[PDB]
Image: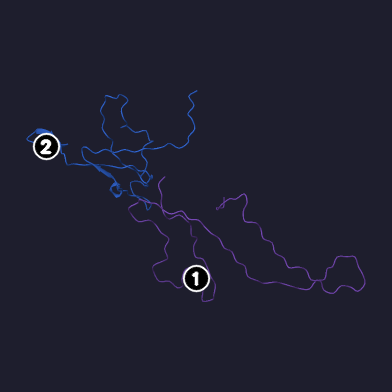
Chain colours: A blue, B purple
């Protein structure tokens, strides 16, 4: 959707020819930011509507300064699917063997 | 701890010795072990071949990495080379860890 703001009057319309891009980091080449207990997961209540979190990452630092080994990543340097309205994305994943959690 | 690969079954020890050659024995029997021997040494060549398996880098890092490099500027002699006197020397220690990988 595109939003148009003139004269304090704001309007929202569809942009039919617009795309979004999606990809999975299947090869684990980006810093993994899940697992740090952040906000922005899907809501517990199904009826709730949610906002997607922004992605950011960290590398080595000395004070406020970078060091030699500090790394920069561009996500646009990965292949991604482009979807218009009417396109969809899916994938399947299998968990590795892991021990049962003890509910006892 | 000093570094390296630890193996239950490492490359085996290889032991080499010159066989003893006795100098002339006495002409009537004596039971004592011989203590007079001809003087000997040996020389030869030895070859070792090893196959190493490599793991290639898979980095998505945009910017360049650190690399081991030879010195750019002029010098009295070449690093990792001989002397005017024919003495090879290794100037610095070189480690293994230049490329980077995320955690």
Label 2 sits on residue = A4
- Front residue of B34 and B13: B13
Label 2, label 1: how far apart the Cα atoms are: 71 Å
Chain letter behind tag 2 = A
Q: For the point 45% across and 37% down, which residue is it?
A: A96
Quadrant of residue A46 within the rendered picture: top left
The total of numbered circles placed on residues is: 2
Q: Residue furthest right?
A: B28
Q: Residue furthest bottom?
A: B84
Circle 2 Cα neighbour tier, 10 Å, few/some/many (<14 / 14–19 / ≥20): few
Residue A15 in the image: x percent, y percent? 15, 39
Observer-side mark, 2 or 1, equals 2
Q: For the point 41% across and 59% down, which residue is it?
A: B67
Q: Compared with residue A9, is residue A63 higher up or lower down, i.e. above or below?
A: below
* A34 relative position to A99: left or right: left
Q: For the point 13% across and 34% down, which residue is it?
A: A12
Chain letter behind tag 1 = B
Label 1 sits on residue = B81
Q: Secondary structure at mark 2?
A: strand
Residue A14 in the image: x percent, y percent? 15, 36
Dots 2 and 1: beta carbons under 8 Å?
no
Q: Secondary structure at mark 1?
A: loop
Are labels 2 and 1 assigned to the same chain?
no
Residue B15 in the image: x percent, y percent? 69, 61
Quarter of the image for the N terminus of chain A: give it. top left
Residue A87 tag number = none
- Front residue of A17 and B37: A17
Q: For the point 43% across and 71% down, which residue is it?
A: B75
- Front residue of A37 and A104: A104
């Amino acid at each position: 959707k595109e939003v148009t703001q003139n004269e304090g009057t704001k309007t929202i319309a569809n942009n039919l020819t617009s795309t979004i891009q999606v990809f999975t980091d299947s090869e684990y080449q980006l810093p993994y930011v899940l697992g740090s207990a952040h906000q922005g997961c899907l809501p517990p209540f199904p009826a709730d509507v949610f906002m997607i979190p922004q992605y950011g990452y960290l590398t080595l630092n000395n004070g406020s300064q970078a060091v030699g080994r500090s790394s920069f990543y561009c996500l646009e340097y990965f292949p991604s699917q482009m979807l218009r309205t009417g396109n969809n994305f899916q994938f399947t994943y299998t968990f590795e063997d892991v021990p049962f959690h003890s509910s006892y | 701890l000093m570094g390296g690969f630890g193996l239950k079954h490492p490359p085996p020890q290889i032991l080499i010795k010159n066989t003893p050659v006795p100098a002339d024995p006495p002409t009537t029997f004596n039971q004592s072990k011989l203590n007079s021997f001809i003087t000997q040494y040996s020389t030869g060549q030895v070859s070792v071949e090893i196959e190493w398996e490599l793991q290639k880098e898979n980095s998505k890092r945009w910017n360049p990495e650190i690399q081991y490099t030879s010195n750019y500027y002029k010098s009295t002699s070449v690093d990792f080379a001989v002397n005017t006197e024919g003495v090879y020397s290794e100037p610095r220690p070189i480690g293994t860890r230049y490329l980077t990988r995320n955690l």
